[PDB]
């Protein structure tokens, strides 16, 4: 439960660049091979 | 409307139409050098001082944008050198009587204009005369607090 | 000799006047002549907090009704309310007012006799003849319309700037938490199971257009889904097709809470940069023309489109730094214009909000997350060239959000200002949601008017606070709250003493009684929907000896009056002129103290006085000589004045931005005395030896018994130790400095980190007490104890390691040290104000 | 709505005392809540003005011509500002359905000695101004379902 408090209070802007970047590339690729984020 | 090109648009306003120029040249647009390897690969060099999130534009035959253009580069101040470092405060002018203190806070600059914000450099503050330096301290944001 | 009479009348002060936490005075006695007060060289005045929180162990304000008669007994001439200091003649058939001296008649339902001392026999039986703070039940003649319910309507900026900074999702979570906290004013807390939260809730979001959220239920009893009605007419505001834009919260519990959950997701993909907040706050006005209430406005930037757009001439908006061509940083005379509103538009709208009994709260949070509007404006014309890169990531300061222009929306309607520089969800979310839950659920009064009277031969020169000035004395408050403090300055009337042989400071014809009284009357409707009259009566005796009136000073109230006067002087001519006035007024006050003090062998002791907690200063005067008390009093004044010189209120321009100084001045003109002295004198506590400062029983850390906080450290760097952690609070923010050589066992107990490099300033505020070790849980006990000791539980904690760029905000708050603003310690500053004296 | 071909375009406006231009477009992230731009039914708004409130007015410097390599599956017949009101029938079929059973009568109070407030003239004005900016010289039919006399604003009879 202490995990859910810490993760809910963390922007993607605060994540250290590459971690946010690979989430953006993976989300766009999953959106590509299913059919605005699904 | 405020600083693209003026003259540069009046040169390529025609730019005979098979190979018309499609980018409108901004206030400080570069020209990347497009050395050709003869193998399909092209290396591009560029030089752009100002502290801003500059945008690389890549064009094919100067007509169609390429890739995920524009790309963002985090251009920023660089290596601290002499000359351009400046001082501000009361230490450039009248000091205190009775030995209270005075401050000659110096702000580190790179080779061309920008404000370096990485602390750690060493500045030789001479104390020639009756003024004798107490402390040079690193503000750790690009300035230095000398007393 | 001639001191026993003074201490009897001083005893009459401490047992009949309004209490300390409601009213606080600069001096307990007053001078008799204008020649005496010019030689005093210290200001005279009161601080008034009519809805102050009552400390446990202290009596609550009693309620007095007048029955079916419906006549509050009042003076005819000055309209001063009945107070325990009137004089009763002809066996109580007549009463002379202690402010204007007229002999009024006693009503027939007020007929009671007198005792042997001239007072009334039922003086303790009726509460308002013995206590200085009373709450009357006002009759129907004081209401112009039926008592309106507690009302709130939230303005949320939903532009692309605000949704990127997380302001839309931080504000919506706070509003939901405050409405469901159970402390909502207007909910009947007198427990009888019935559906009557009379509170009124509306929701308006804004961007380039203005959006209204329909919230009422369907006419057929079904659960209607919430609607979003765009309104793009940002020049002439109207209301869309609904009568459910402003609904009751109890009857619409599910619709309001659901719509708050939908707002962050619905405007999540908004790509609009510009905002029309000026049209949005006008839009809130048309909703509540018939009820009133409070706007909880969350604005990130000034309005660039729509109505009420202010453009500042001269290019002065670039003083904080947005241009690099040599034209705005060489004129310090024009920087004072940056601190005042640049247009007459916002004072006239604040007048319109006042006449509708509507107050506005401001929550101004400019963004720092790389706003794209700073470089994407359409260009044409001429240059190029050369040489990039490598280092220095940003140091992103707060962009100029022009807080000076938008101040009168709260300063003229009794609303509050809450500013967040460089708003991000990791740092300012907890401080924002605790402000929302505190502003909403505190003790609140509505459609308030206040009026401050003084006795004859006295007048009020300067009035400070958040109000509107109607007439000459009538304070107007759209809302009043528990944190509203209004300060007055008093002097002598030289015109009222040249009209006959009555030139002695309100002397009644009963044989002489030299008492000067101030009356604070507040007509307001409480959260339960009834009209109350908040009466505070405070008195000071006329004294002819300067030894009595100087020794009876309150050094904290004297400092707060000098700070508020320095803000006006800086708003009038120059900040540097107000800085000179603060140092000057320190020197004539200290020369008065050395002249009244007969001891000449203590001027060479440049030490610190015995520092008590805030509100425990008039207790250390029982085993000390009067000379020893007054040296420590004026030395404590010089410490607090030197504090505000080094604070953000009077620092040089290059180190504090413009809109930071605006919010510091707006706080210092409306804060209570205990928070102003906390701002000018931060309190410092050590945290690395928490196991040392504890008893042999280790008395369990609960708040039921106080979480033990003995040591208040001095504010100089020589007691700092490199293996230590040190917490500093200044009434606005906490800074937790951690040394490089801190024990790793202590670090794992508090933040759970294995090294100092494993700590960053952003997340380690929430990481305190998480590892559940007893050492770090006691650190969280210290943090929450200083959090809740003040009125509001909203005060951010920015942890600072030794060697980060954010270290200078800690070391600047060390007031005894030497900072980039003033290169003087407290030892040198006493020396400078002693040779000037 | 089912009789029209699945490829045809469609928009919707419901007008009472004020004109509501509904939101059919947008992403799949905000389907559950309806939106409606509101126009004041009793005042004169030109076709130039109406496009300015809705952002449909043609920008003077609106050439970024076909220079997005990576815009995902964007429909090129409609500009993104105009796609929020006009959508294909088969793409906004759920949202155009859900607007319809939500549609109740005019909620503003009608006095018993007065006709209901009706801006039929402004409803055709904002219908035609949107189709000007987005759909110039393209096949459009404005199906006006009116249930009585116009009483407010432009074009009002009694």
Image (spheres, rainbow, N blue to C red):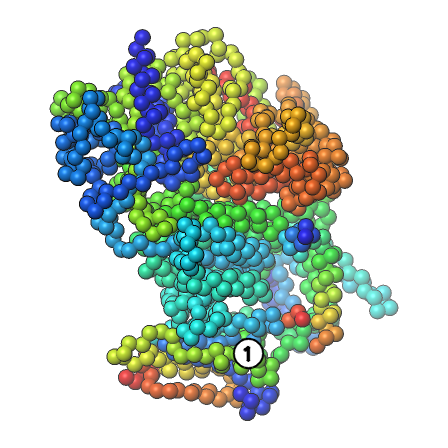
The front one of C394 and D22 is D22
What is the residue that sits farthest to the bottom in this orientation? Answer: D3
Residue at screen point 58% across, 55% down: C165
The x and y percentages for residue D37 are 46, 72
The x and y percentages for residue C537 are 30, 32
- Total numbered labels placed on residues in the image: 1
What is the residue that sits farthest to the right in this orientation? Answer: B39
Element class at badge 1: helix
Q: Relative to residue C42, is residue D92 drawn left or right?
A: right
Quarter-wise, where is residue D74 in the image? bottom right
Residue at screen point 73% across, 65% down: A25
The x and y percentages for residue B32 are 74, 60
The front one of C137 and C7 is C137
**Badge 1, how many Cα within 10 Å: few under 14, some, many 20+?**
some
C457 in relation to C768, above or below: above
Residue at screen point 25% across, 20% down: C33
Q: Relative to residue B146, is residue C561 drawn left or right?
A: left
Name the image quarter holding the C terminus of chain D: bottom left
The front one of C540 and D64 is C540
Does the rendering let one see residue C239?
Answer: yes
Quarter-wise, where is residue D42 in the image? bottom left
Residue at screen point 40% across, 27% down: C558
Does the rendering let one see residue C315?
Answer: no
User: Mark 1 — on which chain does it sit?
Assistant: D
Residue position marked by numbered label 1 in the rendering: D95
The front one of A13 and C438 is C438
The x and y percentages for residue C403 are 46, 47
């Amino acid at each position: 439960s202490l995990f859910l408090e810490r993760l809910k209070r963390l922007s993607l802007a605060d994540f250290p660049c590459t971690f946010r970047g690979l989430l953006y590339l993976l989300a766009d690729a999953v959106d590509a091979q299913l059919r605005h984020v699904t | 409307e405020e600083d693209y090109d003026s003259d540069a648009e009046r040169l390529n306003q025609y730019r005979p139409p098979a190979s018309r120029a499609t980018h409108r040249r901004r206030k400080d647009t570069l020209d990347g050098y497009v050395y050709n390897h003869g193998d399909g690969t092209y290396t591009v060099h560029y030089y752009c001082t100002r502290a801003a999130r500059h945008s690389i534009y890549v064009y094919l035959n100067d007509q169609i944008l390429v890739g995920d253009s524009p790309y963002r580069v985090n251009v920023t101040p660089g290596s601290t050198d002499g000359e351009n470092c400046e001082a501000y405060g009361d230490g450039t002018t009248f000091f205190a009587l009775g030995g209270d203190f005075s401050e000659i806070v110096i702000q580190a600059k790179d080779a061309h204009g920008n404000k370096v914000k990485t602390g750690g450099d060493k500045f030789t503050v001479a104390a020639s005369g009756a003024a004798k330096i107490v402390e040079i301290t690193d503000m750790k944001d690009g300035t230095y607090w000398v007393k | 000799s001639t001191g026993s009479a003074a201490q009897q009348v001083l005893q009459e002060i401490q047992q009949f006047n309004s209490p300390r936490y409601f009213t606080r005075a600069s001096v307990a006695r007053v001078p008799h002549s204008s020649s005496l007060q010019q030689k005093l060289h210290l200001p005279i005045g009161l601080f008034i907090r009519p809805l102050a929180p009552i400390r446990p162990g202290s009596p609550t304000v009693p309620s007095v009704n007048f029955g079916n008669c419906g006549v509050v007994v009042r003076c005819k001439r000055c309209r001063t309310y009945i107070n325990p200091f009137v004089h009763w003649e002809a066996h109580g058939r007549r009463w002379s007012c202690n402010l204007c001296g007229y002999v009024n008649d006693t009503p027939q339902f007020y007929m009671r006799g007198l005792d042997e001392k001239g007072k009334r026999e039922d003086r303790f039986e009726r509460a308002e003849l013995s206590m200085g703070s009373v709450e009357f039940v006002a009759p129907a003649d004081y209401m112009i319309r039926p008592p309106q319910p507690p009302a709130y309507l939230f303005l949320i900026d939903v532009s692309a700037t605000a949704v990127a900074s997380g302001l839309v999702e931080s504000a919506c979570a706070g509003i939901r938490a405050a409405l469901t906290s159970g402390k909502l004013p207007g909910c009947t807390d007198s427990g009888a199971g019935r559906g009557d939260s009379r509170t009124m809730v509306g929701i308006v979001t804004y961007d380039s257009a203005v959006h209204f959220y329909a919230l009422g239920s369907a006419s057929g009893g079904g659960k209607r889904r919430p609607q979003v009605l765009v309104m793009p007419e940002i020049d002439d505001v109207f209301l869309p097709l609904s009568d459910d834009l402003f609904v009751n919260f109890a009857e619409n519990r599910d619709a309001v809470l659901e719509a708050l959950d939908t707002i962050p997701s619905l405007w999540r993909s908004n790509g609009c940069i510009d905002n029309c907040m000026g049209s949005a706050v006008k839009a809130a006005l048309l909703v509540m023309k018939h009820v009133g209430g409070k706007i909880l406005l969350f604005a990130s930037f000034p309005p660039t489109v729509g109505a009420l757009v202010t453009k500042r001439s001269g290019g002065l908006a670039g003083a904080d730094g947005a241009g690099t061509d040599g034209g705005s940083r060489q004129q310090p005379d024009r920087e004072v214009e940056l601190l005042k509103p640049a247009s007459e538009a916002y004072q006239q709208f604040a007048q319109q909000l006042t006449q509708s009994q509507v107050s506005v709260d401001l929550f101004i949070a400019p963004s720092s997350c790389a706003s794209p509007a700073a470089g994407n404006v359409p260009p044409t014309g001429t240059y190029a060239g050369g040489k990039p890169g490598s280092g220095a990531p940003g140091l992103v300061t707060a962009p100029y959000c022009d807080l000076a222009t938008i101040l009168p929306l709260a300063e003229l309607t009794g609303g509050e200002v809450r500013y967040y520089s460089a708003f991000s969800r990791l740092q300012h979310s907890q401080q924002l949601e605790n402000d929302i839950v505190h502003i909403i659920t505190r003790t609140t009064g509505w459609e308030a008017v206040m009026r401050i009277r003084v006795s004859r031969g006295w007048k009020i020169s300067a009035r400070h606070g958040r109000f509107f000035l109607r007439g000459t004395d009538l304070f107007v408050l759209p809302t009043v709250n528990a944190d509203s403090t209004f300060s007055i300055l008093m002097e002598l009337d030289e015109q009222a003493g040249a009209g006959g042989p009555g030139n002695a400071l309100v002397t009644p014809p009963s044989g002489g009684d030299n008492v000067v009284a101030v009356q604070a009357a507040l007509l307001y409707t409480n959260s339960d929907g009834e009209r109350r009259i908040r009466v505070h009566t405070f008195c000071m005796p006329v004294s002819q000896n300067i030894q009595d009136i100087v020794s009876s000073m309150d050094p904290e109230v004297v400092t707060c009056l000098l700070i508020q006067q320095a803000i006006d002087q800086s708003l009038r001519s120059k900040i540097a002129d107000g800085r000179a006035f603060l140092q000057t007024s320190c020197s004539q006050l200290l020369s008065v103290l050395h002249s009244v003090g007969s001891s000449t062998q203590l001027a060479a002791s440049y030490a610190l006085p015995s520092l008590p907690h805030y509100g425990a200063v008039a207790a250390a005067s029982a085993g000390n000589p009067a000379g020893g008390a007054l040296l420590e009093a004026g030395r404590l004044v010089a410490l607090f004045i030197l504090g505000v010189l080094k604070s953000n209120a009077f620092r040089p321009v290059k180190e504090v931005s413009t809109d930071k100084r605006v919010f510091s001045w707006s706080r210092l003109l409306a804060l209570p005395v205990d928070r102003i002295c906390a701002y000018v004198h931060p309190r410092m506590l050590p945290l690395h030896n928490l196991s040392n400062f504890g008893g042999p029983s280790d008395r369990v850390l609960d708040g039921q018994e106080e979480v033990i906080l003995p040591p208040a450290l001095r504010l100089t760097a020589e007691e700092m130790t490199q293996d230590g952690a040190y917490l500093l609070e200044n009434g606005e923010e906490m800074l937790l400095w951690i040394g490089r050589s801190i024990s790793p066992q202590w670090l794992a107990s508090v933040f759970g980190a294995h090294s100092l490099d494993c700590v960053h300033p952003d997340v380690a505020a929430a990481s305190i007490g998480d590892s559940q070790d007893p050492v770090g849980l006691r650190v969280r006990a210290v943090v929450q104890s200083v959090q809740g000791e003040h009125l509001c539980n909203a005060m951010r904690l920015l942890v600072i390691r030794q060697g980060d760029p954010s270290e200078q905000k800690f070391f600047a708050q060390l007031m005894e040290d030497r900072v980039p603003s003033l290169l003087l310690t407290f030892a040198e500053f006493l020396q400078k104000v002693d040779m000037r004296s | 709505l089912a009789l029209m071909p699945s490829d045809a375009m469609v928009g919707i406006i419901t007008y009472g005392a004020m004109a509501m231009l509904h939101e059919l477009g947008g992403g799949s992230e905000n389907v559950d809540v309806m939106k409606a731009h509101v126009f004041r039914g009793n005042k004169e708004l030109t076709s130039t003005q109406i496009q300015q409130q809705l952002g449909l007015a043609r920008s003077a410097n609106a050439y970024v011509p076909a220079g997005g390599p990576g815009a995902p599956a964007g429909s090129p017949l409609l500009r993104p500002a105009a796609a929020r009101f006009i959508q294909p029938v088969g793409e906004c079929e759920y949202k155009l359905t859900s607007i319809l059973e939500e549609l109740r009568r005019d909620s503003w109070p009608v006095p018993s000695d007065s006709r209901p407030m009706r801006c039929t003239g402004l409803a055709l004005s904002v219908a035609l101004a949107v189709l000007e900016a987005a759909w110039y010289q393209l096949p459009a039919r404005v199906l006006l379902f009116v249930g009585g006399a116009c009483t407010s604003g432009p074009g009002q009879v009694v």
